[PDB]
Amino acid sequence: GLRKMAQPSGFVEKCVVRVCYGNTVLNGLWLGDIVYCPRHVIASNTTSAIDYDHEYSIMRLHNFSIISGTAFLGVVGATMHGVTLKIKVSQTNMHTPRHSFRTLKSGEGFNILACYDGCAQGVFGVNMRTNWTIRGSFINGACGSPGYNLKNGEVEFVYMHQIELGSGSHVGSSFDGVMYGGFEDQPNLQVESANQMLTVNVVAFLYAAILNGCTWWLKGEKLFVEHYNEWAQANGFTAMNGEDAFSILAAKTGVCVERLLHAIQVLNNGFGGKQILGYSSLNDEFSINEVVKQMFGVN
Amino acid sequence: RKMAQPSGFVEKCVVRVCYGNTVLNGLWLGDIVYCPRHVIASNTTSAIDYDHEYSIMRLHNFSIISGTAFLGVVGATMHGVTLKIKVSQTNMHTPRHSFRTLKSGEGFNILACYDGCAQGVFGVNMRTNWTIRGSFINGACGSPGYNLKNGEVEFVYMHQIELGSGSHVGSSFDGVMYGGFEDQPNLQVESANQMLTVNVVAFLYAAILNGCTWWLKGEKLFVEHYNEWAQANGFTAMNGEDAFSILAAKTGVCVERLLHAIQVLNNGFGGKQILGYSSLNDEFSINEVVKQMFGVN
Ligand SMILES: COc1cccc2[nH]c(C(=O)N[C@@H](CC(C)C)C(=O)N[C@@H](C[C@@H]3CCNC3=O)C(=O)COP(=O)(O)O)cc12
Ligand SMILES: COc1cccc2[nH]c(C(=O)N[C@@H](CC(C)C)C(=O)N[C@@H](C[C@@H]3CCNC3=O)C(=O)COP(=O)(O)O)cc12
Image (cartoon, rainbow over all chains, first blue to last red; front, side, top):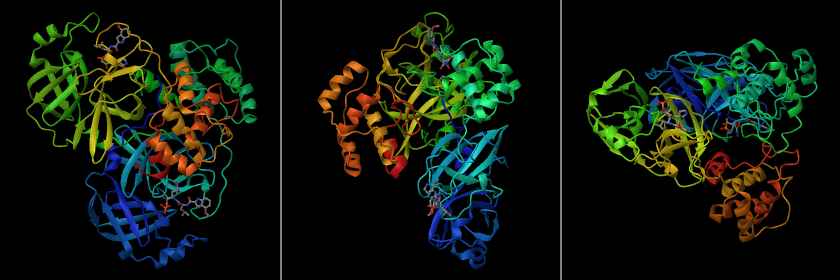
């Protein structure tokens, strides 16, 4: 079958801490001797526009409390970097994993460790959508929850949770302190752009259906990538690219991309009660990488 | 959003178990390694006489690796469809834990492992036909299923086989195969799956709490009439209306209006969608819905 999976969370869980500042609690990420967390933790009043330079100048280090498991950490300094704080603590996290920082591109998959009061509660896989929001599941207290990927024996930290938009979509920042999509960490309504279905993930899904033997939707007609891309601009799908990446899948099946792009056009009107790998409409959750790892064990 | 509970406490308990040329995953708790008994079978190709395989077992064929260390086997005994392998070494990362057998409908977490190393983690439900909708390939056997609850890890599932349908079957850690399936290379057909009605009701209450209510009408379907419709339409009977009384009280919507909606929505969504789903969804339990939206267990 095909299940949306998270990569294991163990390396990340040892780094999550609780960050208290005055009348606000949220989550931080403890790496080396730095704790990363959203800068709005220091905002005393969030019922009007937040002047972060003012909040920063009145900040006093003795109002911080940072808790790892049951241990308090000594706070030594704190600097502001975009929409994040970098808090210097007197102790090094001896469980700091091998890691780097990376900024997600449009459509890329990653993992969210949903944390509360400095303790992890759930983990799930998710895609950065073309409108720079994610479909998460967060309630109050989740700010500072980290997003990550495991690659080559290294943790890549990619997302720090920040805000929930009026529509229910979730916005975070990189650990550089740049908010995805340019959203503001301000208490006021902001509207995101319309979402686009990720065409390359729908193609990979349809290959998966072929390999699992679900072929009823498959015809023999081809739709040229260029003709599809004009249709996608008018129907809320991203353009097609990287057809060469689908070599692996096209070989094992003997079906070409341009036949599936035809199918994408047809199946956008509904599955008519039929179900493809157990879904009743097109799914853009799965990348080529995931299909290929889950079906064949090849990275 | 479907999620899993975090895996850190379980990851340190998974080991790589090799017997001869067969490799799979074991669970290291205390001084015992638990794993599927087919690790000692000579030919996973034809019928297996496990009493014979156990009698010719030779313990020096074992190799058990946790990270970089080798564990020393001192004995092994066979219980149901599992092996309990006693080693010299006690797992110093053993979490507070118990073993529990899942009932029909219950959700749990799977840590999919290969060669003794965790690769992914996802939530599942034990279906009424005693299979789960998983994702596994060769090498996944022994992958553990777990729940985190009341400051301890409950271990509930050991992965064992893929049915010809693609559905997946495991055992509890007392050696009892869920569904009574056999750990043999023969085609076995599970019974027909049923949609879990309590989970579908949980989902519609989730929809109401998020202001998704186009489908909601005023008509009421009494539980006994629904259950008659259910037995003939591949749905489970309505039960445990107790936790739903709480949701009914908060939303003002009685369960009987949702049972009616199920009967109607079963014939398709008419184009529209519910929480982004294009058809009835029974993947979420009432606990998951309450935990995710209100933060309470
Ligand atoms: C009137 O203004 C609005 C209008 C319409 C929509 C709006 N949306 C936000 C927003 O997103 N506000 C951030 C803080 C900003 C103002 C600095 C926030 O609330 N984040 C949560 C996680 C959120 C909470 C529920 N689900 C989550 O993902 C934290 O965890 C961190 O802070 P808190 O734990 O709540 O104290 C303000 C707002
Ligand atoms: C040929 O007759 C059949 C007919 C129809 C359906 C059938 N199904 C099986 C089966 O499932 N067989 C068990 C081995 C038992 C019988 C001893 C198995 O293959 N288990 C996998 C997990 C599986 C592997 C693929 N996806 C998974 O979930 C392990 O992990 C251990 O095996 P490996 O050492 O890793 O290959 C045999 C069979």
